[PDB]
Length: 345
Ligand SMILES: O=C(Nc1ccccn1)[C@@H]1CCN(C(=O)CCc2ccccc2F)C1
Ligand SMILES: [Cl-]
Image (cartoon, rainbow, N blue to C red; front, side):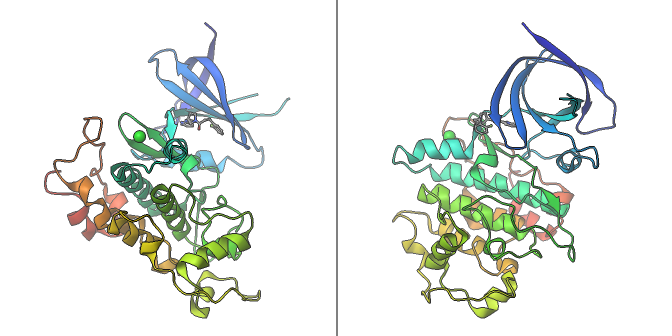
C-alpha cells in the first residue's frame, strides 16, 4: 500500500507537468545505464516501466529528446518523465509496460527444439520495419536493433521497438562512433570500424533478427569481430574489393579466406518459405546502399499474408493495426502505399 507521488511532464504534447501517483514498485532489471522499475499507476491501474538514469548536468538527455518527438504504434510510448535523486540528479522515463520481448519468446521456442510459426515471424518483422521506416524518416538511427529491444504483447501480437539509449540522428558528413550495436547484430561496416555509416545498419540488424527467428539461433555468432566476419563470409561469400570500399575500412589490410557464395536455400531448414529467404538476401548485403529500405521491406511479398483480408491471429483475435500509415511514414517512397495499404483497409 506504498504510494509515490511526483510532478511529471507528459512525453507528447506541451510541457505541462501534472501530479502522478504510482504503486507496487519493483525492480525488473539493471540496464547498464541504470535501473528499470515496474509500477502501477494509481488512477488508471495501468502498468508502467520506469527507466532511472543519471542526469548529465552539461547537456540534456539525448534519449529523452528523441523519445518526445516519436509517436507511433510500434514504438514504446513515453507516458511521463520526471527528475529525482548521492546528491546527483536522476532522469526517470515512465513508459507503457509491455510484458514480453522477441528474445524471451524466441528462446522458449528455441530450447524446446521448435521454430516460431511463420505468421508471428511475419507479424513481428513487419512491425519492426514500420518502426524503422518511421524513425529513419526523421533521420534517426536506432543503432542497437536486437531481439531484447523488441517488446511484445502476446495477446494482441503488437511489437514495440524500445531502448533509444544508443539512438542518434545521422547527418551525412558528420562522423559517428563505430562501437555501437550489439554483438551478432552488427553490420560489416561497423565491424570494419566505419564512422560514415547510415541508417542501413538497422536494416542489417533487422535481417539478423529475421534469420535468427527462422534458424532458431543467431546466424552470425562469434566472440570477436574476426569470428563474426568468417560466419558472414561463409554465407555471403568473400566480399569484392568494390564491396569492401563501400563498407569503408580504408587503411587496414584485407586478407580473408577466398570462399564461394554458399547458396541461401541451404542456410535454412528444408520447408522454410522461399520469400523469407529472398527477403534475408536483400537485407543482409555487404553494400549498405544495396539493402532494402524499411518501407521496401514492408512491401515485400513475404508479408502478403498480412494484407490478406481473412488473416487472423492463431488465438482467434484480429491482427493489430498494420495499415494506418501516415505521410511522414511513407515519405521515403509514397507510391508504395498502393501495395502497403490493401483494398479492404
Ligand atoms: O522489461 C519489460 N518490459 C518493458 C521494459 C521497458 C519498457 C516497456 N516494457 C519486460 C518485462 C520483463 N522483461 C524481461 O526481459 C526481464 C527483465 C530484464 C532482464 C534482464 C535485463 C533487463 C531486463 F529488463 C521484459
Ligand atoms: Cl507467441
